[PDB]
Image (cartoon, rainbow, N blue to C red; front, side):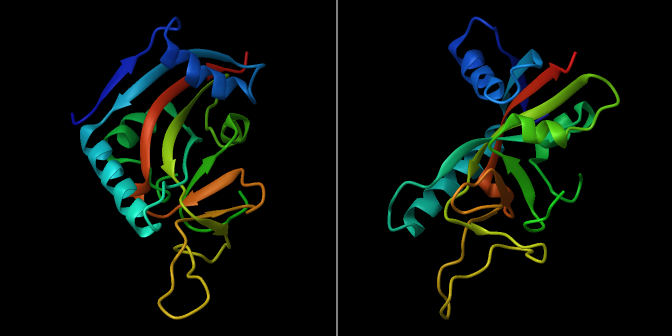
Length: 182
């Protein structure tokens, strides 16, 4: 309705860039399809959010990453339209949407009763992160009154592999990847 999914050719740069990231940690699985998600509304919001975060970061570029999110085929179109939402879908670093450095992590949270799975690659404004906590419903504030708040939570500040996002405006669902464990 407000989005399109464009199937990419395996001979394209774009396909192979996405494939490369997946293959970093799931070389033993087989990618069957990659689709580019085009949602102008979600894109406009995301780019605005990025601009606002840059201003609030003393005018410096925002930490922005391409991160994986395990899904199921049935919820793909809902995400493409409305964005990710944590209260639709292990160790908790807060009550937000989880995004992983590694596809292999996302594979663990990708629900299927068959060998065929789906995950997103998403563009994520992680900004300034802090270690999360099961009780967090938003990123905490830094010490001191009306000081800065963080932008995301992580499992580890020194070696972050999981990012928790509490604001949909910080995510753009970029690619849908279908693969098999066969």
